[PDB]
Length: 116
Image (tube, rainbow, N blue to C red):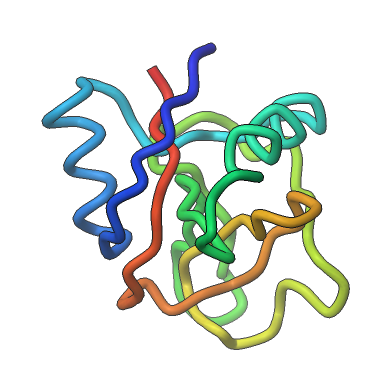
């Protein structure tokens, strides 16, 4: 799997289409700790505090489940302390320090990681 850091600040919806349109790929799915760490290393030189990953919440009410926008199975999560269930939104952002994930409102411009 290859990861590409796009430093331009885009909303989550803009970032997913751009990966598909510019790089023929998707927002990164993260299936284990080694990938999370490799990405963390790739974003450590970002002055931006958070990056978009391909994680989103789907469904309603009690049937709320996490999904990858590439459709792969959700088998790993590296949540920050007090994350998720924070009500901060339906999209997932990786913290550039420590690689821990946080919920963010999809209407935020962040850098993002494509996988290809």
